[PDB]
Image (tube, rainbow, N blue to C red):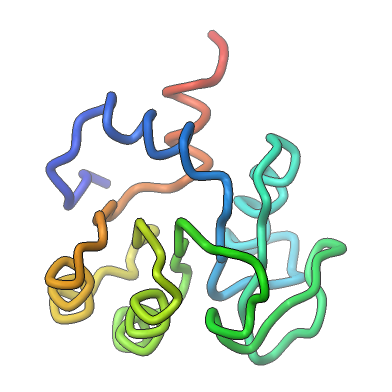
Amino acid sequence: TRPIDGLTDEDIREILTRYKKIALVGASPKPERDANIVMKYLLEHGYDVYPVNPKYEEVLGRKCYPSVLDIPDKIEVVDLFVKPKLTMEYVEQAIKKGAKVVWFQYNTYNREASKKADEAGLIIVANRCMMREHERLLGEK
């Protein structure tokens, strides 16, 4: 699972440090799904997580929205857990929402969606996991 973006460990560490407002797309109440595992970890580590998934109204005690734009609070990072073909719609939303970073989790990257995000000034993190990166870059031993 090699990173697709060209950012350094320092860049990622900075992103995880400066941006605490996360819109987690593809949120799921299922404990065994990566979206749930990562969201749970983020909540336990002080992040403001706003789950997004039209199929759910609440995930891990957090109100779940059908779209990123429906979220009342400001969003800085859009953490994607959906299939590549579905990221375009959410990238367009992230753009409208004024997000600062688009984060493509494992097996979700789509070059067309990423390109639009990049042309819009969005920072791109790709083929990395927010939890994995946090653990290895900001966690202990």
